[PDB]
Image (cartoon, rainbow, N blue to C red):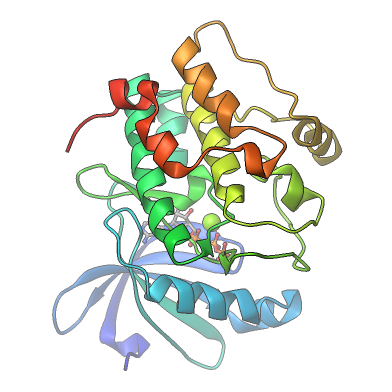
Length: 264
Ligand SMILES: Nc1ncnc2c1ncn2[C@@H]1O[C@H](COP(=O)(O)OP(=O)(O)OP(=O)(O)O)[C@@H](O)[C@H]1O
Ligand SMILES: [Mg+2]
């Protein structure tokens, strides 16, 4: 349905493992969007041609205001192009670098949007598994949008696919190569909540082997400015036992969330 000559390419929006994301405009409608470019050679070498099929299949059939839209795809002989909704206020990763940390109001609002979006995914037995600040984008009204469904799968799942990045947002069960379900995203929510308030994830380290030990043992401490209410929600989500992690409804109902989350 689409080809490269249908778009006017603009500036790079960001960079990923298999290529860049560019701002683009559809020549006929003048529709501004983003094009995620992936090199075929790289996907073959890494053996991630599946995963890319999953990202397209899963994300194309999701419709939620806090989930980034995947309008379609196309390809040539060398590259694969994903047609995405353009998020104009960038990443939560960049916002965090600018502010250093976020207040309870901004944190609680982001956690609400994330829990709402994850509740919709989990209803369709879709587990994201790669909820990282670089994958959380911002709409024109500054609302959070979950993006990058490359690691998404239908639950329950095991993993043969090896992890090549930081272990900071991954639960003990994923790190150990064990079985897992939707409770993986509940752990990631707790890691993000801590990082939004503190400015660094609770198991950050100089080495991968050290991070693994901290995650495996659930070895974290709160700075003095973290409030009782915030400590309570983070400590409820960062449970070694996946079955002990709360339901997303309990996250949305938490007193600290209700008290600081901005109302639409
Ligand atoms: N629609 C978009 N609007 C604005 N910026 C975007 C958009 N999509 C991606 N970006 C930017 O490009 C970066 C890379 O995008 P993305 O997470 O989709 O790629 P990836 O990490 O390489 O993919 P994968 O995990 O599937 O292998 C983002 O972190 C962000 O900075
Ligand atoms: Mg990414």
